[PDB]
Image (cartoon, rainbow over all chains, first blue to last red; front, side):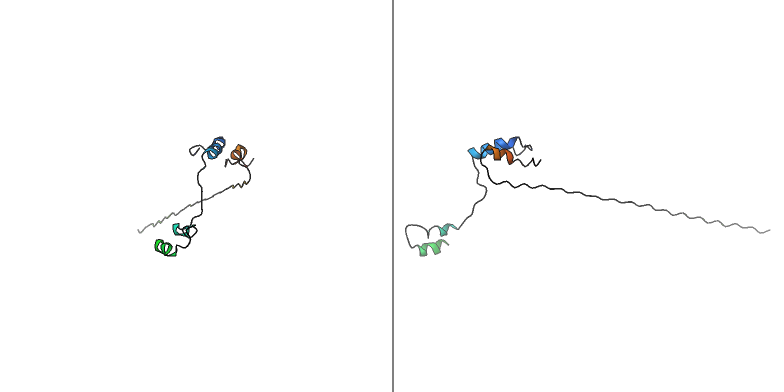
Amino acid sequence: LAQNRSTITYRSWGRSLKYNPVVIDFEMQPIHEVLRHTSLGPLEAKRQNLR
Amino acid sequence: GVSVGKCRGILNEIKDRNKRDTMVEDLVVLVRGGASEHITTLAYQELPT
C-alpha cells in the first residue's frame, strides 16, 4: 500500500491495522517520575539520584 | 574637379518577451467516527465522493 496509490488498497490496509495496530503517537514522562507513584512509598533520595 | 560622397548607416533592434504562470490546488479531508472496514475504505485519501 505504500507503493500503491489507489483507494483499492485502503480496505486491506484497514484490515491489517485491525489485525496488527501500530503505535502512531504517545505522551511520555521521565522514568524517575513513575517511581514516586509506586506502592513502596517514599523514594525521594533514589528519585533525586536517578534524576 | 572636386567630388566626395559621405554615407553613414546604423541599425538597432531588440525584442524581448517573458511569461510566467502558476496554479496550486489542495484538498484536505477530515473523518471521525467508524472502526469497521467501511471507514477504512472511506479513509482513502484518493475524489471527495
